[PDB]
Image: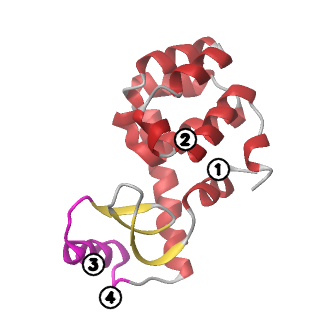
Amino acid sequence: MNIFEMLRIDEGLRLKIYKDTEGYYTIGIGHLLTKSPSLNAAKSELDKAIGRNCNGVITKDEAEKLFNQDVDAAVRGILRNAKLKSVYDSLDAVRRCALINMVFQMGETGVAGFTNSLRMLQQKRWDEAAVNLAKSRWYNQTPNRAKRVITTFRTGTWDAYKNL
């Protein structure tokens, strides 16, 4: 199991514009297009992102390309943020996947906001951090996905996805 397969399970693949759990316009493997309410504004972002007139629809290939770029940017964003890089560097390979997943879903800024939980991961207090991470809007809004990420940090194994 690797970051790509992990994120593909959590986000799904959709070749037509769609609204995400938060109601935002998305396409592919979790690629947010705009927080704007206009399907029009979305179709324009989409065409800008792909480099063609898509009319709201893309091919598998295009989805995977956006996915590659987004995971790359998620990693680069962690490495560029001091708070984040320091946790990332302290972690083992599996747990590293878990922090990347959070960053991909909620952006650098958002994850950097989990001050206390980051401190615990850094200290390697797995159970404590799992409990603290569960006290968040994130967990209340998308609980099955959050639990899978949480378990990953708690155990350091891919058990939560070996199901799926």
**Residue type at the position of mark 2:** Ile
Using a 10 Å C-alpha cutoff, classify the residue at mark 3 as few (fewer than 14 neighbours), some (14 to 19) or many (20 or more): many
Does dot 2 land on a helix, a strand or a loop? helix
Callout 4–callout 1 Cβ contact below 8 Å: no
* Residue that mark 1 sits on: 3
Q: Relative to 46, is 161 on the left or the right?
A: right
- Give x and y (percent) for residue 76: 46, 42
* Residue that mark 3 sits on: 43
Q: Nearer the viewer, residue 52 or 46?
A: 46
* Residue that mark 4 sits on: 55
Q: Which of marks 3 and 2 is in front?
A: 3
Callout 1–callout 3 Cβ contact below 8 Å: no
Q: Relative to 15, is 45 on the left or the right?
A: left
> Which comes before the other along the chain, label 3 or label 4?
3
Quadrant (top left, top right, bottom left, bottom right) of the C terminus: bottom right
Callout 3–callout 2 Cβ contact below 8 Å: no
Give the Cα distance between marks 3 and 4: 7 Å
Does dot 1 land on a helix, a strand or a loop? helix
Coloring scheme used = secondary structure
> Which comes before the other along the chain, label 4 or label 2?
4
Q: Is residue 114 magenta?
A: no
- The image quarter containing residue 43 is bottom left
**Residue type at the position of mark 3:** Lys
Q: Relative to 32, is 96 on the left or the right?
A: right
* Vertical position of residue 109 compared to residue 58: above or below: above
* Vertical position of residue 149 compared to residue 124: above or below: below
Whether residue 133 appears in this view of the structure is yes
Give the Cα distance between marks 4 and 2: 31 Å
Q: Does the magenta stretch include residue 38?
A: yes
